[PDB]
Image (cartoon, rainbow, N blue to C red):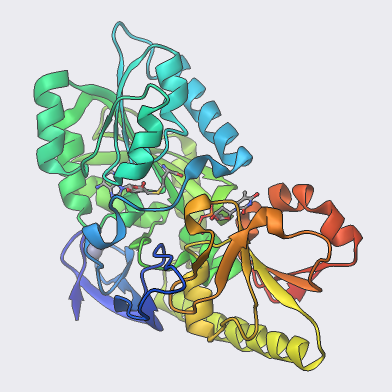
Length: 405
Ligand SMILES: Nc1ncnc2c1ncn2[C@@H]1O[C@H](CSCC[C@H](N)C(=O)O)[C@@H](O)[C@H]1O
Ligand SMILES: Cc1cn([C@H]2C[C@H](O)[C@@H](COP(=O)(O)OP(=O)(O)O)O2)c(=O)[nH]c1=O
Ligand SMILES: [Zn+2]
């Protein structure tokens, strides 16, 4: 049995996705076929209800000099983070000399707006190649992990932060207690720690098991985040559901008692309770539906091949490593994957070794079908790929069900 990373409680497994590769490792075709693998399985703590993986991948295996995800590759996300930055400039960052720290700034998708407002800030970005892209934009960035000690160092030299923000980062960090002790050291007494990450309620409702992989250690809910804050000196004082990345919640933590929670917190807590979101039976039902999607997806991809139809994929997502490796889906069924990220092109996907080609290569003559791994970006991708569909090309989705359209 594994100990909960939040409270030390016991974690009960409910889904085992088997042996998996690093999701963001893209190999050159000529590289030795040797990969780090680990067991990906997910459990729920008995005491605090935190849904979490049962085996940690060490941070430095995932995040380092060549980490390939470039946030600013999606226009929807550029706009989503610009808007969030302007909202913070209008509310939490209005004093004399405000200071915002972002955990996991990546290429500077959010902090660019803060920098262009002349607000003092610092991005933590331990993946140095994307850090350098943020620094090219004028952003102040430290190429370190946020944790207790690096938070203390920033408090020492920069003073308190009015906002600490983390998007698609806190749930990557098993050492969430260290991060919380760092937020406690660094946050102003009237500041907020705000984070947004894939939401358990969405994962369960959409059976989007691809949101489960090495970099998503936690699948947060309002119930577990409320517990986590409380256990650590903070309080959950707002929630906002976001449509990005398949469904997220943005959580606002304050020092306990310093602000009164919005009605939104209790409403979401009560909906989670009402729908038995984190009950083990629900979480098992979700696991059973994950297997049903596997079996339906592979039967379709097999039938397409038997009927002489070409199939490729669209989006070399981190997410897709779970799909191809759990389902057994390799270049015999999905010939290539198209992606706009230069450092993933002319590479093979992890585990399954499907070749990745630039999206500019997805063009007449089109394949019959494209398996949409970037299904959280459907609207943005399809708007750019209307010629494909007008030609008769069709999308295969596996969220929330296997279907073609
Ligand atoms: N302890 C830590 N502190 C700060 N950044 C971290 C971290 N562990 C991982 N990261 C960074 O967290 C990032 C997660 S990817 C998400 C990036 C971006 N905020 C977005 O929403 O698109 C990677 O860039 C990774 O290097
Ligand atoms: C929005 C968009 C993304 N992509 C690619 C870039 C990324 O490698 C991938 C989308 O990944 P994303 O869904 O953002 O994250 P993850 O890697 O966590 O699953 O799809 C395109 O090729 N075209 C596009 O229009
Ligand atoms: Zn716990």
